[PDB]
Length: 36
Ligand SMILES: [Zn+2]
Image (cartoon, rainbow, N blue to C red; front, side):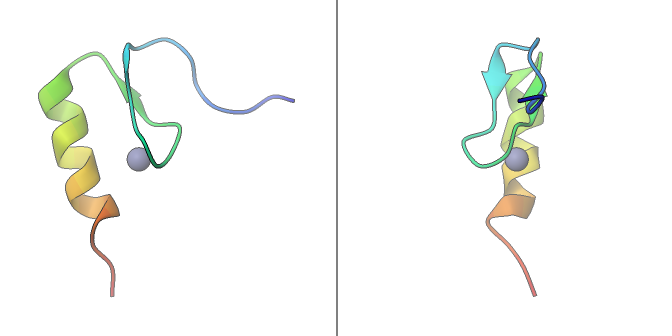
C-alpha cells in the first residue's frame, strides 16, 4: 500500500514527514501542536 515517504532518518511522530536535519523536524512540529 503506497504510503509514507522513506529516505530521511528523522521522521515525524505525527505524519510521514521526514527530514535530513533534526532542527528542521523540530519546526515542523511547531505546526502540528497548533491549530485554529
Ligand atoms: Zn508531521
